[PDB]
Image 1 (spheres, rainbow, N blue to C red):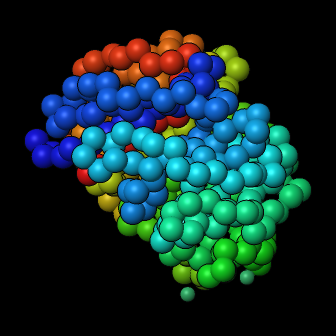
Image 2 (image 1 turned 135 degrees about the vertical axis):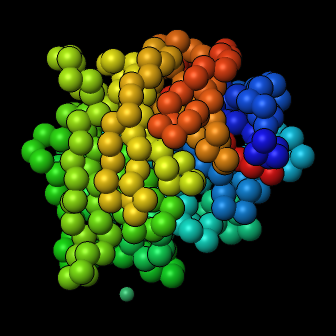
Length: 334
Ligand SMILES: [Cl-]
Ligand SMILES: [Cl-]
């Protein structure tokens, strides 16, 4: 048993709801709360100190702060701040002092300061990042990695102590033409990053510091079955905290591709394909890495899977109704 007590948060923008579930060590979910958001909530992130759930809402572009009740993970609206564009992805720095928002439509990444955990007036906005789709702080907290999907690049910005962003040298790393870099995760060992490319459903493995001190792409892998000929539409990517397994999903095929991760994190290998909730845009892993929770944007349900064996293949355990068009999942241990 993972001996953990956890909460699962899901975003259902088409019904303007956030669902809160208690997740027991045995994988069973129980509904804790349903929140009516003041608009369509899409991205969500738990603060590093676990006091808040920060979420992105439209059409009144904002990051909303919901205070988390420690015992059961329930939410209470606590504050908000305006954003310069519709939030596509939300995250924080390693120390929970800033919220980063990537806006696809406004092609920008912005920084929101936190004061006693509450979001304040935007302190900077970096525009000109067409298709800006995520902002991902490096393991060492110095560099914000920002996929610009329509520019086939991941922009690299130094984050100052005061929350400002400015281009590094080099200012970016590039993907193959038309790949459409979207979401990424870093290996727990802090040495590699993994980016899922939407438009060609591929995963790029990025070495963060090679012997010359440079960032290099050291592997590119197709996440689709060899017999796939449809429209590639990849979405999310997550790695288990034990570093053994990596998962990515495609919205057209409605699959989660299962990858093994070499011991040093430098090599991925496809282990299998798991049919999942229809049109999976968002999923996540629990804090133990024993469970994967996937949302179906066209199923209106989440599915809980056991992660099993040395390959990390998935075995469905349960299925739960959420709101309409669920597309974001996060899990908090407490
Ligand atoms: Cl630099
Ligand atoms: Cl250094």
